[PDB]
Amino acid sequence: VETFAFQAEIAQLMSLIINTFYSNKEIFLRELISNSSDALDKIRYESLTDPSKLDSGKELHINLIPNKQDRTLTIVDTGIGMTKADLINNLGTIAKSGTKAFMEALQAGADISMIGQFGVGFYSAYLVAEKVTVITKHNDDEQYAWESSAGGSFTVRTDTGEPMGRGTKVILHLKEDQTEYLEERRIKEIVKKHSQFIGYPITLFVEKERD
Ligand SMILES: Nc1ncnc2c1ncn2[C@@H]1O[C@H](COP(=O)(O)OP(=O)(O)OP(O)(O)=S)[C@@H](O)[C@H]1O
Ligand SMILES: [Mg+2]
Image (tube, rainbow, N blue to C red; front, side, top):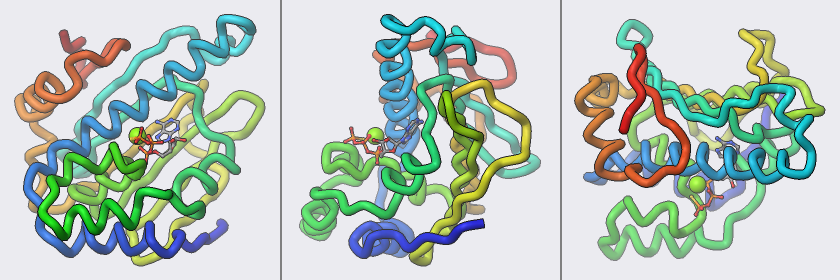
């Protein structure tokens, strides 16, 4: 297991998200679905000139899986996935140019929904989750698990769980006061409100394709 420090301003942002009250937390799901859709675009376009990139799975889609027993909400996609370098670089150690400006915007009264436009949308997960685990598999790399409960660091380790063909699984360990995001009707209303025009199928467990 390898431990990494979040870049200083990313750590500051995560603390701000965790310790300051914001309404409109529901946009976390929009941000994660957008990341899945971006990842699905990437593998789709790559496959146009190299169809073998889909040997690890041809279906391009997103699954939403609430688990009330475990208090988790999982967002799974069959997008391009992340290499180990991708996880380390893109999910915490490299500075984002918009982080400081976003925190200044929040202090001035901006809605938390603006988080994606500032280039730090992933961290919206911490509005509702005490811990986030990201399991990911990219072609020509092994499967990895990234994990953080905030506090300034994350870990990365080779994953020996259920093999994915290709893509990313974001597992949100929800805070005790945010279990509304495990409810069927709640998930449907948020998807309808915020993710209506995503260009890949979205399926809610346990069985239902959302249109
Ligand atoms: N499901 C995923 N599959 C592959 N890569 C991902 C996934 N989720 C996040 N990432 C990576 O994490 C990076 C950071 O995600 P975000 O913080 O949402 O920022 P961003 O999506 O690059 O910027 P936007 O368009 O303003 S939300 C992405 O650019 C991807 O490289
Ligand atoms: Mg994003």
